Length: 369
Image (cartoon, rainbow, N blue to C red; front, top):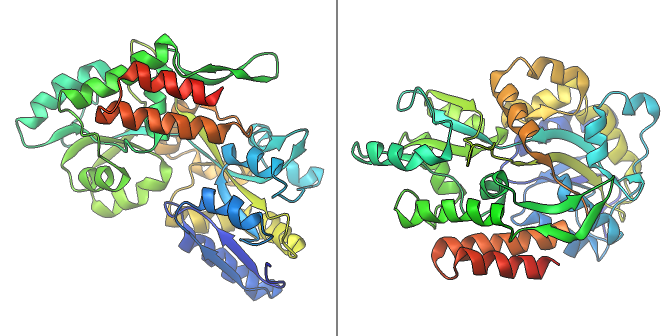
């Protein structure tokens, strides 16, 4: 069972866990309870397993898309901010954490992928996906590459798959139809085919993952990467002269990243629900609390209006929101888990040559519906 009188918090390893720990120290200093912050691997899978036995963290941080499934499984406590508190955060962030007519988490920040590029290697970054092969040939001649990004997580390839028409669940008239999925449509196939062609033509390697792409960009070996706000700290440290901008278009249409709202849920089994609420409302979701996390690894466009006013002046955040507006907020429905697993396999299989694009997406579509 969860220990009474302290808070255990889980957040992903790419986020500001050390900054969050600093907020936890302040909470302890002012109100008493120790706060322990951990970042277990595969925590979005780990959480439902341990929470099911009445264990795990008091507070779980993840993008909002995983939360409907958690709520459906009975793993989340009710969250009931009063009106005054609700007014401090943007409406669309609350909507991302609204499930079956109730709020199931506190929204923290809006995340969207952007194109990150090295201004020294590439002062004028490409506006289109289609110009990347020629750009890579030019760079390969100089012992550099045009682009490296994580190919193991479909989050990163989805913007291209969606560009020409792929979609997860059709949303019509305020409702998601779980039987209308757009994973093996022509648009999805076209986008995935373009990616696989980049691999076939040696412009990218199928085994490139988060670590490899981060290192390559930060070491100045590749002119571009695709990543989120959390990644900007390590780039700063590397001293690479970078920019953050609009993702390239595909077939003249914008890349459409799936927008995540980093959110904090309270474990239904926590005996510390009131401590968790106080921590989230009165320590974390304050200008000082978000600054502490943000200075560690950037959060993106925060949900808290007062601090977002400060962050909005950052051109990287502006680029983040431009890409967010061209994309779509993720559904939070329980079927998102199945969606992501199926698309993950489809992209890896197509990228590695285990299956054709058409067969990979056909199988994913089938698995999802």
